[PDB]
Amino acid sequence: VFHQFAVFCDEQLQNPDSLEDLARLQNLKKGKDEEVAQLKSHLAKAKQWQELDQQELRRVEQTRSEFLKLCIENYLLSLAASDEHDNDALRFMALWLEKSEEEVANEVVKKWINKVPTRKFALLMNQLSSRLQDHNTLFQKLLIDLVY
Amino acid sequence: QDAIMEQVFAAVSELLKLHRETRQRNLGIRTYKVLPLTSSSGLIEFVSNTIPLHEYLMPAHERYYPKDLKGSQCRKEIANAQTKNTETRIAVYRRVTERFHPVMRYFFMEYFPDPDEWFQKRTNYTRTTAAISMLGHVLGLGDRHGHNILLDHKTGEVVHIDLG
Ligand SMILES: Nc1ncnc2c1ncn2[C@@H]1O[C@H](COP(=O)(O)OP(=O)(O)OP(O)(O)=S)[C@@H](O)[C@H]1O
Ligand SMILES: [Mg+2]
Image 1 (cartoon, helix red, strand yellow):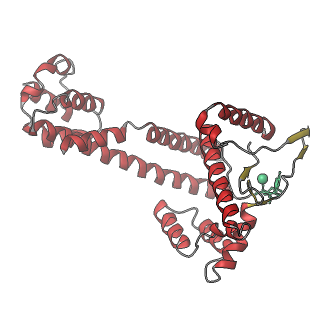
Image 2 (cartoon, rainbow over the protein chains, first blue to last red; image 1 turned 90 degrees about the vertical axis):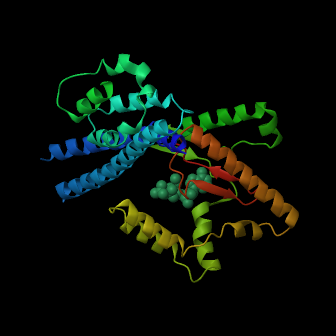
Image 3 (cartoon, each protein chain N blue to C red; image 1 turned 90 degrees about the horizontal axis):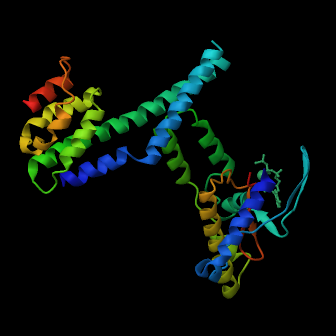
């Protein structure tokens, strides 16, 4: 069940349709902000439409953030449950290292990382020990503890 | 633009004739002729015995459902909620389509009362709609409102114009 749900959410993240939608909304926001920067009810309507674009973009990004949370959480739960799916460690690792800045990913990982057997990560020490740094971030406090 | 795209669509529909399944069903599109004279004028072929989809649908909606909203009332209710969040837009749209029922099935019952002719013409409608739907997806065709779609009331098929 957990692998099913994690693979679903992952596929919903790397969807070409949704990525093109996010890119289109981003270019729209950028161009509308530039147009507002030109003029500074013309300004009134322009900034009203800019605000509507902002609301749409917040909605889309919140959807993507929820998908990211569910993906990481269910990968970690699936690794801790059975041995059927063990290349989920490589996929979880790629997904977590891409999002080392987004603190939502780090909160989910902090919550669920201590229940996975460390034998699932044992063969990925070339990639884990290459990202070690002393920065006092949460990502580093999780990575150093996992390597330890 | 319209003439170039009409030519492109005609060429792809000619490609459709080389395959057993689309040729067996005569899947293709109906063409017309655009002739640009200058950068500001042209001659467009008026397709013979069609009727625009909107000109049939807006009178029929009030002829068959006198208690429903008019078409202009639905248009205005949808246009007023255009600068609002998506939740309010979807709620207004559901509210409007709960008081607006389709009437297209009568186009065939009032132009073809013979069941043999009726069945053949409704099949023509469905097939030409399917072909133009796939072909216009593949080529990104847009601007598909009710004034660009004509209903041929002799053969039952749809004609798409203004393909720019
Ligand atoms: N080639 C055509 N053959 C038959 N009917 C046509 C043809 N071109 C347009 N029409 C219809 O004749 C009417 C003339 O419309 P037009 O003035 O060409 O543009 P329009 O779509 O009606 O108006 P807008 O502002 O573009 S929505 C409309 O009802 C069209 O559906
Ligand atoms: Mg037109």
